[PDB]
Image 1 (spheres, chains in turn orange, yellow):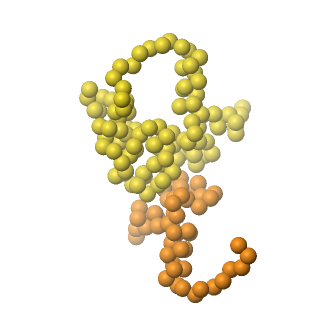
Image 2 (image 1 turned 180 degrees about the horizontal axis):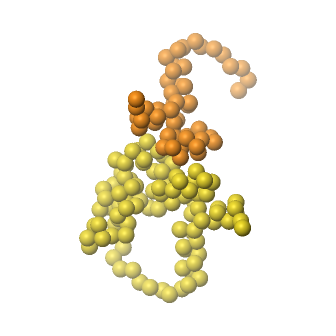
Image 3 (image 1 turned 135 degrees about the horizontal axis):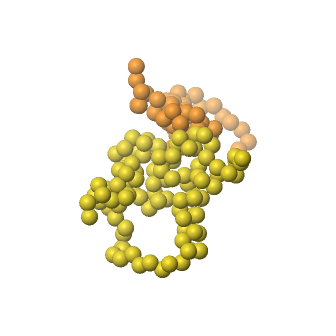
Length: 51
Length: 102
């Protein structure tokens, strides 16, 4: 990769943030503190605990 | 033959795809699969030792040590339901003395 080009597609930007940062396959590195409390990712927070 | 009076029952009940700790957490699913337990398959199939009818004793102690070592003491992934140990910084029994000694 040499250059990053902006496409400005918001719907594709949401779906990517979702799969990469919000709900990934494995938890994001150095998150053992979150995993110990019972949450691997951001999506798991509201699926297990709601208020 | 009693399913409850079987030593695998708590591990096979935990290692279930219907348990939110496996269906949502891939790390825990891989831990179960490493111990041959398939969480997708039914409970009877989970506790079942596939293609095995009789267990024969060979009495080899050195071979018995190397197996307990690779299976229970120092496995590839941590043994299922050990998030409490992993949080303190220990995946397995071998890691205890490699990180902390007294």
